[PDB]
Length: 10
Length: 257
Length: 29
Image 1 (cartoon, rainbow over the protein chains, first blue to last red):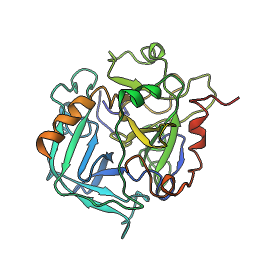
Image 2: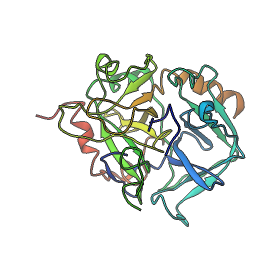
Image 3: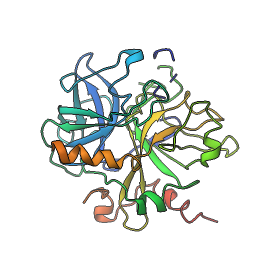
């Protein structure tokens, strides 16, 4: 889920 | 890299930028583990639920890299993959395990003061070093603060360095709520530790190389995979067991290069 | 030659935050 999270990025 | 500091010319000659051609941009970083072989997070190459999914052509790779902005005219490198290689038992579905991928540099790079390889562990090294409290250093150009945005507070000008301790496996299972496997490890100081730093957005794929006091070498102990944010008093990043999966790592090298 | 940064080790330079690395394997004071 990579590290800034589910929902996608900003 | 949350709370870290700016690199120095030559201090991580194995850090590579996973820069897609167009939308001309950067999704991650990886590391130089041969004349022509580069390894990274899998999430960094194949994520369905966000329909992330690339192919050689899709991306292009760069080296010699200090400033995250420009064009490192004659210290930098770049070549495109010949073939990407992921790990056939990867969990983008569950917790993102065996978060590992490798890429047979379409062609081969020739090293210098600015591009030089990293070596992979041996149980010996995989084991003197991968221990509670023994710090490791994580690099990149990732997001200076939790997923947000600023040539400031968003992303750095230059390459970011942080060194973090390993987390007592127990404590690790109690930062998250994600089913964490004996294949992933966690870095980063404690709430109480009174000091902070971490890895953030587009830090991913980025290395977790430590230094063995035995031979003064740099051993890529980890590979950036996940977090529930950036620099939370209460959690620790989660990296890939480069050695656990060192097995696989070998097979594809010895079968296609 | 791997693991040996040609701008430090490879000519005994010591990156300003590496010494901090060591004092964890043998824990400082």
